[PDB]
Amino acid sequence: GDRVADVIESSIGDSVSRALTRALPAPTGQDTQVSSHRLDTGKVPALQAA
Amino acid sequence: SDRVAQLTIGNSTITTQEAANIIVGYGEWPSYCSDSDATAVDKPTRPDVSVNRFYTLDTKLWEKSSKGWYWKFPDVLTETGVFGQNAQFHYLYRSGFCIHVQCNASKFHQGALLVAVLPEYVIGSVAGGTGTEDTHPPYKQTQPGADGFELQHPYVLDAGIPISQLTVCPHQWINLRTNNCATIIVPYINALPFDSALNHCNFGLLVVPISPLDYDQGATPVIPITITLAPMCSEFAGLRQAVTQ
């Protein structure tokens, strides 16, 4: 019998594995979409952080 | 954000992390010529991706006693790549531009640059010192090419017009404390729908250091300045054989 709050609300025993990622079907290579020029500030996909 | 930017057009890309927004010349984007404004009858060509790309022309050194430089458009590109080939082979021409100026230093360097665009920038001469001589600027001064040319009297801009009023033209500042790049977008400026790309120059680009460069001994003394530019919405017409000049 559980009566104390720290045991009632406890998270001990969670046996399921939290998965951040999922598998998606990929029978062929990915397609390429049409693109055009872009001249704006604040949105930069070239710069990263390794 | 606002200080970070990435400009991509054609097969080229420019990234920056110390931007200061983008200036659009006279609040207008470059555009094609309409059917009610065109006057020639033949179909013009629009090569698109092969000419609308960033071209890096050359690099200049900024010193403590530099006076300034100017470049003429599209004289800088009349002999570079597919754009130069099309400009040589065709009689007519029409395009805008996107100018990016690179200049970086450390947090212990100081100085300021004024980057401005002045249309129809006719260069005057000193008229022989006294002023009784009727001289005209030589070829290397009126049309310096892609290598640029250095100002002799930056206070008058070699035309008898004060530099304190150059900010009425589309402009940006390169202050080393804040930014390290500048971008100005220029539409097509002319009184004619099409004009020659070899005889006529539309505008000139001015880079004059208003605040002198200064640093302590031991820091890096070589501070370069770089010019990058990309034509926008280019058209050509009147095809014939190529002409050198």
Image: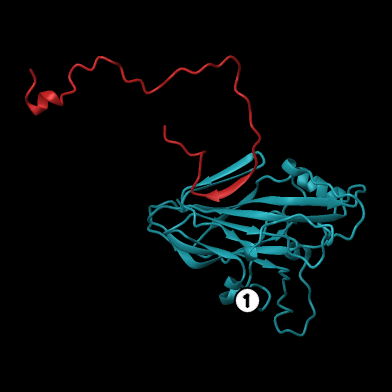
Chain colours: A red, B cyan
Quarter of the image that includes the C terminus of chain B: bottom right
Residue B97, percent across and down? Answer: 68, 55
Q: Amino acid at mark 1?
A: Val
Asked where in the image residue A17 lies, by quadrant, the reply is top left
Q: Which of these two is toward me, B121 or A16?
A: A16
Residue B152, percent across and down? Answer: 63, 70
Q: Residue at x 68, y 45 (%)?
A: B53
Q: Residue at x 74, y 41 (%)?
A: B50
Residue B96, percent across and down? Answer: 71, 56
Q: Residues within 10 Å of mark 1 (few under 14, many from 20)?
A: some
Q: How many marks?
A: 1
Asked where in the image residue B194 lies, by quadrant, the reply is bottom right
Q: Residue at x 17, y 19 (%)?
A: A12
Q: Chain under label 1?
A: B
Q: Is residue B17 left or right of residue B122?
A: left
Residue A5 visible in the snapshot: yes
Q: Is residue B120 left or right of residue B4?
A: right
Q: Is residue A15 left or right of residue B165?
A: left
In the image, residue B91 sits, relative to residue A31, either above or below, namely below
Residue B135, percent across and down? Answer: 78, 76
Query: What residue would you read off at disc 1?
Result: B156
Q: Which of these two is toward me, A24 or A45?
A: A24
Residue B150 visible in the snapshot: no
The local secondary structure at tag 1 comes to loop
Q: Residue at x 46, y 63 (%)?
A: B111
Q: Which of these two is toward me, B17 or B110?
A: B17
